[PDB]
Amino acid sequence: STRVAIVTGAAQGLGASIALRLADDGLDVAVNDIGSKSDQLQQIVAQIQAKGRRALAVPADVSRDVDVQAMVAKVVEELGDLQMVANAGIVLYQSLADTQLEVWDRIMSVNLRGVMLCYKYAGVQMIKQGRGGRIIAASSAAGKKGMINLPAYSASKFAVRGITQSAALEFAPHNITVNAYCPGGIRNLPFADPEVVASLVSYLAKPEAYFITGQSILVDGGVLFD
């Protein structure tokens, strides 16, 4: 009766810290990233198995409908889905004056479309199981206050909040919460280790966090307030 998590963009940084914290929390974990970080994904898998948990690498492009559907199906087959962390994202700096559609669409394809497809296939699987669930996406400080030279990035992280609130309403009758984290300075502003984001995701993923839904929470050391 062990709960199962998927973490996307989990080869390093925030995603790896979230995956290893959920494993420490007692969850079995499937880690996703792009194919080229397959070796790093295997390292994360071995560290989760060293904690006595079950683990699976699921390389996939989260911007592709078929990839995300197959990724959730492979996790259901292998691990037996209670938490989805839609963490994959890219940051590119490019002014609006200098905006190239291929940068604009690439940011939207991973940061927003990827989140939507993870929200949809996790939700559909959790509705099927009838035991509720936890859906959590990476927003950003840039999703609460737009940033100079990050128009595409800012647009994509505001959009994550919009679909989080819409999804939280749609999935509430099935006892699935949908929340987002908005990190600030993660390694003169405050800065912190990625553990502080893993700590927040860990809390939102818990059974006792069932009454928090549609929320986007700032973990930035008090730079923005909501």
Image: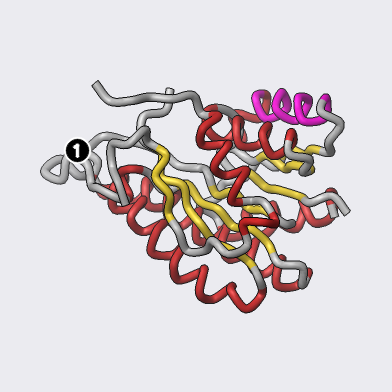
Percent of width and height locating residue 160: 41, 56
Q: What count of labels does the image hold?
A: 1
* Residue 104 in sight in this render: no
Percent of width and height locating residue 182: 40, 45
For residue 142, what is the image quadrant?
top left
Using the image, determine if residue 201 lies above or below residue 120.
above
The front one of 35 and 76 is 76
Q: Which residues are magenta?
A: 40-50
Residue that mark 1 sits on = 149
Of all residues, the one furthest to the top in this rendering is 188
Percent of width and height locating residue 179: 51, 57
- x 55%, y 55%: residue: 64
- x 51%, y 51%: residue: 137
- Colouring method of the image: secondary structure
Left or right: 216, with 204 as reference point: left
Q: Is residue 188 in the magenta section?
A: no
The front one of 182 and 121 is 182
State which quarter of the image contains the N terminus.
bottom right
The front one of 73 and 157 is 157
Left or right: 42, with 93 as reference point: right
> Is most of the magenta stretch helix, strand or loop?
helix
Using the image, determine if residue 18 lies above or below residue 115.
above
Left or right: 62, with 103 as reference point: right
